[PDB]
Picture 1 (cartoon, rainbow, N blue to C red):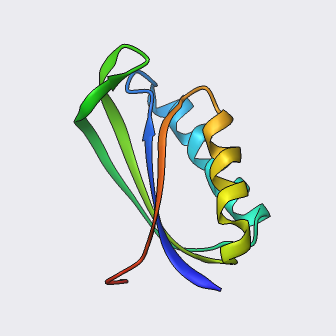
Picture 2 (picture 1 turned 90 degrees about the horizontal axis):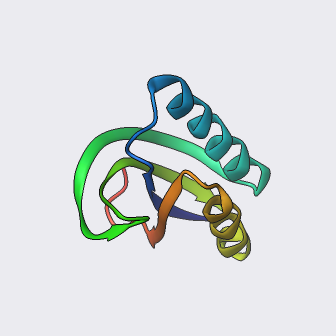
Length: 97
């Protein structure tokens, strides 16, 4: 297994209720692909490098996970289908918590 950082940007107009749901779905998907979720951070609202879905900002979520490298891409695709997920970026962990 390898340790990765998953950066997710969500629709910025969700209320705390919808937000919590998206988080559970993300967690379940990562775990269904063999991931051990080590740390989860809610970063909040940021101005995006470029607008997505016509929105100039997004709600950021960060995850540190350990999972099979052969499943990373499949997991990322799964995450990208959700309508409220605007952007997904997976990088190899360099300085883990």
